[PDB]
Amino acid sequence: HHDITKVDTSGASEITARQDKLTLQGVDASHKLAEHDLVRMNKYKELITRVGQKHGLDPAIIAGIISRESRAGSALDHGWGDHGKGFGLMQVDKRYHKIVGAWDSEKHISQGTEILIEFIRRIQAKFPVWPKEHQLKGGISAYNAGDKNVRTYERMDVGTTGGDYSNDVVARSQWFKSQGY
Ligand SMILES: [Co+2]
Image (cartoon, rainbow, N blue to C red; front, side, top):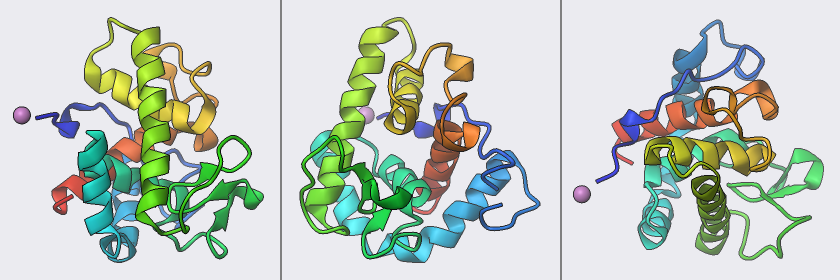
């Protein structure tokens, strides 16, 4: 079994924390942001689990993505975020994909998940000697900012939204795993 606790994370940046108006830094901030989304996330947990299983990705990582992208729906306007570029719980960029499903649907969660997997694949080809946990983290960074932006493992969030995208996602994911995802 893949153990996401083994993925390294320094959690959220100062910029990100300015979101729920937090004095907390890093992993503490990611954990608080995640906690704030737990009730909304539970509405989708059955779908999140099933999609994760079908695609072979930890459901807790899907939850981390959904928390970061949409605050489990709270940050969207009728399904839309990112000035309209992003659709759904996982904020699939409509400009680059034909959107499928309702904004809170299994089909949507499956689409976002498939896109993430494809990024993880690209990072695996790019850095074939990185451990699997690192290629996972790198694929998550690429989900925000593209695989070209992912170079040094230690700097993969430089140039992502908040300067912390995969670190924040991973830390939130780890929190959701502790809450049974
Ligand atoms: Co196993």
